[PDB]
Amino acid sequence: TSQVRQNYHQDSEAAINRQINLELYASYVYLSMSYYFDRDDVALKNFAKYFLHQSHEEREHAEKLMKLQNQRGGRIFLQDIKKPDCDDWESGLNAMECALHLEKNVNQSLLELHKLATDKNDPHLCDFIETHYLNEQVKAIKELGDHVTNLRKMGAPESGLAEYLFDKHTLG
Amino acid sequence: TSQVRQNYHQDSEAAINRQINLELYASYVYLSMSYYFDRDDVALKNFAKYFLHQSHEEREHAEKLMKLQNQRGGRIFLQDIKKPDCDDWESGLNAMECALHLEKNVNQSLLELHKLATDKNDPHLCDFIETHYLNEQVKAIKELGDHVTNLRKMGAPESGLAEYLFDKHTLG
Amino acid sequence: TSQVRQNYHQDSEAAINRQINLELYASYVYLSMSYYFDRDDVALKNFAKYFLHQSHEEREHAEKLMKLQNQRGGRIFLQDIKKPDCDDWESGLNAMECALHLEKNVNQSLLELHKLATDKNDPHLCDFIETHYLNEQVKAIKELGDHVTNLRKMGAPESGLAEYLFDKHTLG
Amino acid sequence: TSQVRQNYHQDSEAAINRQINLELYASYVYLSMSYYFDRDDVALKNFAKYFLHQSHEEREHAEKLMKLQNQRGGRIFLQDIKKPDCDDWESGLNAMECALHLEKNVNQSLLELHKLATDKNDPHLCDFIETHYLNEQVKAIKELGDHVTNLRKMGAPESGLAEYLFDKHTLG
Ligand SMILES: [Cl-]
Ligand SMILES: [Cl-]
Ligand SMILES: [Cl-]
Ligand SMILES: [Cl-]
Ligand SMILES: [Cl-]
Ligand SMILES: [Cl-]
Ligand SMILES: [Cl-]
Ligand SMILES: [Cl-]
Ligand SMILES: [Cl-]
Ligand SMILES: [Cl-]
Ligand SMILES: [Cl-]
Ligand SMILES: [Cl-]
Ligand SMILES: [Cl-]
Ligand SMILES: [Cl-]
Ligand SMILES: [Cl-]
Ligand SMILES: [Cl-]
Ligand SMILES: [Cl-]
Ligand SMILES: [Cl-]
Ligand SMILES: [Cl-]
Ligand SMILES: [Cl-]
Ligand SMILES: [Cl-]
Ligand SMILES: [Cl-]
Ligand SMILES: [Cl-]
Ligand SMILES: [Cl-]
Ligand SMILES: [Cl-]
Ligand SMILES: [Cl-]
Ligand SMILES: [Cl-]
Ligand SMILES: [Cl-]
Ligand SMILES: [Cl-]
Ligand SMILES: [Cl-]
Ligand SMILES: [Cl-]
Ligand SMILES: [Cl-]
Ligand SMILES: [Cl-]
Ligand SMILES: [Cl-]
Ligand SMILES: [Cl-]
Ligand SMILES: [Cl-]
Ligand SMILES: [Cl-]
Ligand SMILES: [Cl-]
Ligand SMILES: [Cl-]
Ligand SMILES: [Cl-]
Ligand SMILES: [Cl-]
Ligand SMILES: [Cl-]
Ligand SMILES: [Cl-]
Ligand SMILES: [Cl-]
Ligand SMILES: [Cl-]
Ligand SMILES: [Fe+2]
Ligand SMILES: [Fe+2]
Ligand SMILES: [Fe+2]
Ligand SMILES: [Fe+2]
Ligand SMILES: [Fe+2]
Ligand SMILES: [Fe+2]
Ligand SMILES: [Fe+2]
Ligand SMILES: [Fe+2]
Ligand SMILES: [Fe+2]
Ligand SMILES: [Fe+2]
Ligand SMILES: [Fe+2]
Ligand SMILES: [Fe+2]
Ligand SMILES: [Fe+2]
Ligand SMILES: [Fe+2]
Ligand SMILES: [Fe+2]
Ligand SMILES: [Fe+2]
Ligand SMILES: [Fe+2]
Ligand SMILES: [Fe+2]
Ligand SMILES: [Fe+2]
Ligand SMILES: [Mg+2]
Ligand SMILES: [Mg+2]
Ligand SMILES: [Mg+2]
Ligand SMILES: [Mg+2]
Ligand SMILES: [Mg+2]
Ligand SMILES: [Mg+2]
Ligand SMILES: [Mg+2]
Ligand SMILES: [Mg+2]
Ligand SMILES: [Mg+2]
Ligand SMILES: [Mg+2]
Ligand SMILES: [Mg+2]
Ligand SMILES: [Mg+2]
Ligand SMILES: [Mg+2]
Ligand SMILES: [Mg+2]
Ligand SMILES: [Mg+2]
Ligand SMILES: [Mg+2]
């Protein structure tokens, strides 16, 4: 056993490794989405910028969990990062909808992680999740919902003008 | 023979003179396009600004080739600069499409020039073309493609509103 | 066909997608190595810092290739990012040796990519690889070789003192 | 009853008084350790500096708990501060090992305190412990573990050179 390990259940350790993979997966989804908008036949540079930033944030989320694993004396075990579900993201509205679904999926995993930490009476892990993950998720989900709403109201995805104007006035 | 000349084939010298003419031609096409947008019955000042800048860049491309010719000990031979294919450029979208076609034509000529330089084992000329021309062309073509895409998606050329808003938010 | 595509062979497009995956793989290897050194039973923070920086550089390499793909009118196709070969990296010396092997493997792939670009007479792609990848690889390989040499000379991996002092005076 | 008291169980009040004593005890252990390293026959000034800083931090931990007691309307009851277990701390490695054991003991007490607060549904007290104590403990334990590891790897306690170099390059 690690000399630092205390009150850190093996189930929690395993769940943290699963969460690391999921955060890296989310980084990959956003990376794919970003460069879709950089295509010459899509050409929405602020959608590209927005999703690249979200991608980099997800990687920071993963790295902080790796740091946590070591802080508590667990051992990092990495798995393949699966490719995203789509190669072609169809439209700005569709990409925002997929991002919303992704963030709610990552949130559900974080909530299950917190429930495990609660079941194992690990208040340090509970605090870590609450302080660094749960409100960030709520804010991300709200922002994506807001974006979906505006795109729908403006007439996307049929209106290429709506996508263009949203790119310029909300994402730029 | 020029006291400086070394490893510089007469075919390369001639091809450089042809490229000088083509770059000046491209400058002239963009000059014509620019002032079309300055017409009182067209009145898109940022289209005018954009194309005038592209015109001035083409002249810089020509002057750098003139400098190259002398650097290598070749002799500059100038020809008439042909007037552009159109007097009336029809719309912002049509002008962007013509610019895209022009830039791909200039690129093809540069690629043929590079192949000649390769065939004659002239690595200095190869480097000159690669370092100062080829990526600039790729970037210009990508930018023009992006512009065409947005104008089409926004509803041009039928939508005068699309042209106006593109002028203001992308070119301004 | 993409409106921007010119002189860009389908084989080159495919090879660029393969290179994107390899660069992301290299990012993952370095990420794994970094956090190994952050373990409480390893505890070499400058090894951790060094490898995390290398990880972030590899991701930048991947993103630039994604940008290239779109610039030339190719289409990005992503694959799973394989987990690294090891979970436990054994020592500072062993990790440096693995990094050296990785960088030489990535270099070989870049050289094969350049040979394809040469075979297809794509001087823009040749220049891109030469300007942004090949010297960076040569410098990385030389630096890693230098590091391996010093660790060996100092008495690693048997000397934990050698690893500690190298961490402090070369990597810090 | 205090005019401010609300949802503050008598068991929690008593447990806070016990924690105040333990934090002062930890301050005393580190004070003793610090001046051991200031002995002319030990003479490791950065070990002395490090432990004196840890001593002062423990006193701040105690004072914040005293403030908490009054904030919630409990009453502070003080007990003797026991002398540390050792007069002679043997070596830098041994002192770091004793500090690690101390911090894990203080952590266990904090975890028991948090469980009491949970059992009595006192979310303010739960938050206080999580926000101001639990991560500080995890970080302290990780840092001490890191220090023990490096000293062992470098050849302590037999190597007086290892202790000297660690003092200079990690603690200085
Ligand atoms: Cl445990
Ligand atoms: Cl367990
Ligand atoms: Cl997993
Ligand atoms: Cl796997
Ligand atoms: Cl699978
Ligand atoms: Cl998902
Ligand atoms: Cl349970
Ligand atoms: Cl709990
Ligand atoms: Cl919000
Ligand atoms: Cl908020
Ligand atoms: Cl919004
Ligand atoms: Cl507007
Ligand atoms: Cl010659
Ligand atoms: Cl000749
Ligand atoms: Cl001519
Ligand atoms: Cl003529
Ligand atoms: Cl003629
Ligand atoms: Cl043309
Ligand atoms: Cl020939
Ligand atoms: Cl050559
Ligand atoms: Cl570009
Ligand atoms: Cl570029
Ligand atoms: Cl555009
Ligand atoms: Cl092609
Ligand atoms: Cl082809
Ligand atoms: Cl692949
Ligand atoms: Cl795959
Ligand atoms: Cl496979
Ligand atoms: Cl490898
Ligand atoms: Cl071939
Ligand atoms: Cl070639
Ligand atoms: Cl070098
Ligand atoms: Cl160099
Ligand atoms: Cl070195
Ligand atoms: Cl009460
Ligand atoms: Cl009570
Ligand atoms: Cl007490
Ligand atoms: Cl007493
Ligand atoms: Cl007693
Ligand atoms: Cl103790
Ligand atoms: Cl109870
Ligand atoms: Cl509660
Ligand atoms: Cl830490
Ligand atoms: Cl932390
Ligand atoms: Cl340390
Ligand atoms: Fe975000
Ligand atoms: Fe951010
Ligand atoms: Fe995340
Ligand atoms: Fe997220
Ligand atoms: Fe330009
Ligand atoms: Fe310019
Ligand atoms: Fe040009
Ligand atoms: Fe041009
Ligand atoms: Fe590097
Ligand atoms: Fe760097
Ligand atoms: Fe790379
Ligand atoms: Fe590399
Ligand atoms: Fe030194
Ligand atoms: Fe401390
Ligand atoms: Fe401090
Ligand atoms: Fe404390
Ligand atoms: Fe402490
Ligand atoms: Fe809680
Ligand atoms: Fe909290
Ligand atoms: Mg998973
Ligand atoms: Mg699959
Ligand atoms: Mg328990
Ligand atoms: Mg918060
Ligand atoms: Mg001509
Ligand atoms: Mg004529
Ligand atoms: Mg020859
Ligand atoms: Mg260049
Ligand atoms: Mg591969
Ligand atoms: Mg596998
Ligand atoms: Mg060919
Ligand atoms: Mg270079
Ligand atoms: Mg006590
Ligand atoms: Mg006694
Ligand atoms: Mg109650
Ligand atoms: Mg906190």
Image (cartoon, coloured by chain):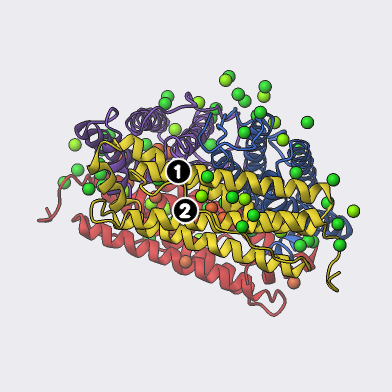
Chain colours: A purple, B yellow, C blue, D red
Q: Amino acid at mark 1?
A: Cys
Look at the image and tell me in which quarter the C terminus of chain C lies: bottom right
Considering depth in this image, is A23 or B122 the residue closer to the camera? B122
Horizontal relation, residue D74 to residue A12: left or right: left
Query: Do we see residue C76 in this rendering?
Result: yes
| Residue D98 image point, x, y percent | 60, 56
The residue that mark 1 highlights is B98
| Residue D172 image point, x, y percent | 63, 72
Query: Do we see residue C46 in this rendering?
Result: no
Tag shown at residue B29: 2
| Residue B147 image point, x, y percent | 40, 44
Q: What residue lies at 27% left-to-right and 37% top-to-bottom?
A: A161
Horizontal relation, residue B39 to residue C148: left or right: left
- Callout 1: CB less than 8 Å from ligand 18: yes
Q: Give residue D32's quadrant in the image.
A: bottom right
- Quadrant of ligand 36: it is top left
Q: Amino acid at mark 2?
A: Val
| Residue D71 image point, x, y percent | 21, 58
Pointer 1 indicates a residue of which chain?
B
Q: What residue lies at 79% left-to-right and 47% top-to-bottom?
A: C100
- Callout 2: CB less than 8 Å from ligand 18: yes
Pointer 2 indicates a residue of which chain?
B
Give me the C-alpha separation between circle 2 and circle 1: 9 Å
Establish if A79 lies above or below C131: above
Establish if B110 lies above or below D71: above
Dots 2, 1 in contact, CB < 8 A? yes
